[PDB]
Image (cartoon, coloured by chain):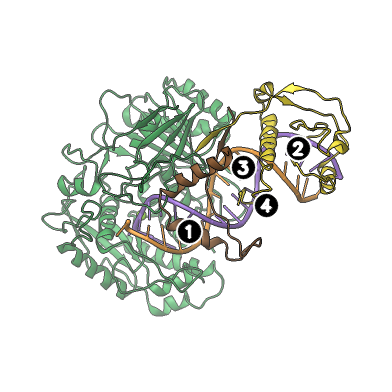
Chain colours: A green, B yellow, C brown, D purple, E orange
Amino acid sequence: TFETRIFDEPELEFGDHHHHQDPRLGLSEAGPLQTFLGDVIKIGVVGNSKTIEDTRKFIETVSSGVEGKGEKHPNMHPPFPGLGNQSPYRCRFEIEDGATAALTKSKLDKIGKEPDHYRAVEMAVDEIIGELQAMDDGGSRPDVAIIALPVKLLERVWNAKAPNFRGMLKAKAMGLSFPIQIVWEDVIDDKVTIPQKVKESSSRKIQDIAGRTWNLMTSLYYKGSGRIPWRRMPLEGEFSACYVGISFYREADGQQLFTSAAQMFDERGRGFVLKGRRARTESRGRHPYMAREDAKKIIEDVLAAYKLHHKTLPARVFILKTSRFKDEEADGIIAALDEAGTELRDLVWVQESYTARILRDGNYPVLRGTFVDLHGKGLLYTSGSMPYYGTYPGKYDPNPLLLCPHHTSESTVAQLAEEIFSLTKVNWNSTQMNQRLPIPIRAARKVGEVLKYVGEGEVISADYRKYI
Amino acid sequence: NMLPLTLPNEMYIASTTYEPRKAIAVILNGDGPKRFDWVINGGTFWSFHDPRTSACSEIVDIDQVEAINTKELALHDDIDEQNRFSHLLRQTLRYQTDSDLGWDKDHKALY
Amino acid sequence: QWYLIITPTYYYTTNGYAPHQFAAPLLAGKKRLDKSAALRGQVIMWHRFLTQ
RNA sequence: AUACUGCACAGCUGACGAU
DNA sequence: ATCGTCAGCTGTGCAGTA
Ligand SMILES: [Mg+2]
């Protein structure tokens, strides 16, 4: 029989050393980890007048406060504690007049009944980018720009009537001074209906009036303030580390392959650094995996960033990858680490396409945090039933992960599993607790999803506020 | 959901070579009794015995039987041999299956 | 110690032995209403199938 | 594309045998 | 010139919030 373990629920760190494990309750009790020095955050809105009025009504409505959804599960549906003296962010959001643009009906008609699926997206993105450029060059620049898409505009760039509108929008908006956030006209009022892509009989489904706000205002605060709301809780007596994430993506046409990396590491005070890179390392082959010199370059850039910030070198160079480590990749990584002079190192392949499952008796699945050591490999469950929520928030048997080291790591299994289970709840795009993937993979995927549409010879930035 | 297996003792190896996949297909249409637990690698038969009393001597041809225990076969740490061993286990799972049919072409199911 | 892994699933036919054109959405509809208790029972049923 | 989970489908990469 | 085996990786769409 194999040896099993059950991991505890990880705790986060909010302001003034509050501990707690729920983002919503911790934000409502102690507030953000990094408090904003100002008092107001300015927001700019772009769209037709109906969307602007809906957005204004929405923020003035949610300023007073929204009650909860249900009574059977109090923790899973907490009420939003207003936006005022009892705000969870200890700040205010204020939409200033004059920092608001508009799009004429004739201009949208030009992006209406127009042929081809690449020209119309081009006209829409260049008009929106030019309007934002004209807004930014004045004296009413906001801290975050909200793009409220009309219902009609969706029928030409998203539904039916082929690139990604969001990808080209983010790629063209990379060269700005403030990040942007896109809404879909049904988050701001519960009276509109957007049809689906292939079948028009159904429609989109929205979470809740109280569930929208807990994510939207958190993301808006992060994008418009630049301060991290929460972070993982460091232990006592652990070594200094630096986490790197590797991923691969294919371009729009040609089915060649590329490589993306993410460069998390901790901070001296109370902070957390999470950023991408500043280059793309060619398109060497349409296969997966990576070459040797690219791995050398990635490791060198990561160590250069850590040396620039901390004025020293880290003691752990933890590496995660979505594919099996070939011999040349490991050779390059080991050569770079040995030339740099670091002693501790871990290389882990995270696998999702496995078939072994754990079955228990009863109407509810296995607890979140069960680990089974399969003769060197590790089966870890990051989804399932939780006692804090009081139920299992899913619809089927959850999907476990298989962790496997490349025979040269300096730490044993059931410690890498503990670190990966610790690293999953840090995601400032959602407030839930049922997230499966750790952040070094999701960050690289989100970076690549926008880096697909950057043309040759353009400039790119390491800012994470321009990829989410 | 794991399940252990226990492999048989003896393994039979032949040296027939003039039989591609097409030849063994067109000979398994007109084979009579159906056992369906052989593989083709080129110059080898690689089956679980029954070389004469199985209506398979048209490809066996009473070749020089290399009686080798399967205990050394599973220990053969080679990927190319491991894929063929898994192929033989998969094809032997296709026995005791005509009573329950299944396995159309793609879903790898046993309906 | 060769190991076998079983993963329960469903196969749809129109009647007897014939493919169904609308075979894709029935799997999702059956998997959506399932619980986490039938899978273990199906697994031990398959084990009893193979052992007997 | 306020969000996450679960499922489905489609592509195309490596190692092995010959026509 | 594609056909068989073995292990994989990405995109593109729904349902459901327990
Ligand atoms: Mg977002």
Q: Chain of mark 1?
A: C
| Alpha-carbon span between mark 3 and mark 1 | 36 Å
Left or right of residue A213, residue B9 in this image: right
| Alpha-carbon span between mark 4 and mark 2 | 18 Å
Q: Nearer the viewer, mark 4 or mark 3?
A: 4
**How crowded is the residue under tag 4: few (<14 C-alpha within 10 Å), some, or many (20+)?**
few
Q: Report x, y in % for residue A96.
A: 21, 65
Q: Residue at x 66, y 51 (%)?
A: B101
Q: Chain of mark 2?
A: B
Name the residue tied to disc 1.
Answer: C30
Amino acid residing under circle 4:
Lys
Name the residue tied to disc 3.
Answer: A287
Q: Report x, y in % for residue C45.
A: 51, 44
| Alpha-carbon span between mark 1 and mark 2 | 37 Å
Circle 4 SS class:
loop
Check mark 2 vs ligand 1: CB closer than 8 Å? yes or no.
no
Amino acid residing under circle 3:
His
Circle 3 SS class:
loop
Is there a contact, CB below 8 Å, between mark 3 and mark 1? no
Q: Residue at x 51, y 35 (%)?
A: B2
| Alpha-carbon span between mark 4 and mark 3 | 27 Å
